[PDB]
Amino acid sequence: PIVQNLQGQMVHQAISPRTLNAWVKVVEEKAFSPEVIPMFSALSEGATPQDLNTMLNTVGGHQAAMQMLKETINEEAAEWDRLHPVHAGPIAPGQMREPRGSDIAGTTSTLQEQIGWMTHNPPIPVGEIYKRWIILGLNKIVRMYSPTSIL
C-alpha cells in the first residue's frame, strides 16, 4: 500500500496485518482459486515489492505454484523487452535507466529504486506492472489447475 505524503511525496506504509490475515484466511478457504486471483490483484492494486513479496510468501508455499509464477513473471519481462526495446549504452552521470521489465522484476530494482521509477517522470507503473505480473502467474497457476475450461 502506497500513499502520497501531505507535502508532496510518494511513500509506502508497508503491508498490513489485517490484510495479510484476511488474505491467509482467504487462501485457506480458497487455495489458489479463481476467486482469489481477483481478490489478490485488487488487494495488490498498487503494492510494493516487499508487500507483494510478503503476500506471495504468505501463500501456502508451493514450489510448483511459485515456479510457474516465476516463469510467468519472466515472460512478462521478456514481452516488455519485446515491446519496448533498449540499448544498454551510455548514460549521464546520475541519469536513470530502464533495464526493461527485468527492472520491474526487482532484479535490478529494489524498494527505493522501484519507488523512484514510480516516483520519476514519467512515472513508471512498476507497481501496477508487477501486480499484473504476479497476477499473471497466479492466473496461469489457476489455469493449469483447471482442465482448460474455456468457451
Image (cartoon, rainbow, N blue to C red):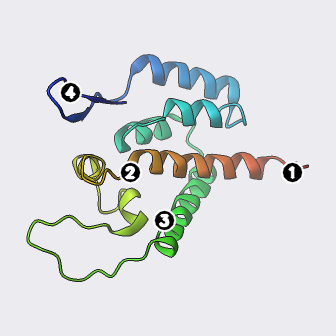
Q: Is residue 26 left or right of residue 9?
A: right
Spatial distance from mark 2 to mark 4, Cα to Cα?
A: 19 Å
Q: Position of residue 133 (x, y in %)?
A: 53, 52
Mark 2, other Cα within 10 Å: few <14 / some 14–19 / many ≥20: many
Q: Is residue 89 left or right of residue 66?
A: left
Please give the name of the residue rendered at 51% of the width and 71% of the height, measured from the top-left corner.
Answer: 83
Identify residue for label 2: 126
Above or below residue 7? Residue 69 is below
Identify residue for label 4: 5
Please give the name of the residue rendered at 45% of the width and 16% of the height, measured from the top-left corner.
Answer: 18
Q: Amino acid at mark 1?
A: Pro
Q: Amino acid at mark 3?
A: Ala
Spatial distance from mark 3 to mark 1, Cα to Cα?
A: 27 Å
> Which callout, 2 or 4, points to the residue nearer the camera?
4
Look at the numbered disc 2 and give the secondary structure of its residue: helix
Q: Amino acid at mark 4?
A: Asn
Identify residue for label 1: 147
Identify residue for label 3: 77
Spatial distance from mark 2 to mark 3, Cα to Cα?
A: 11 Å
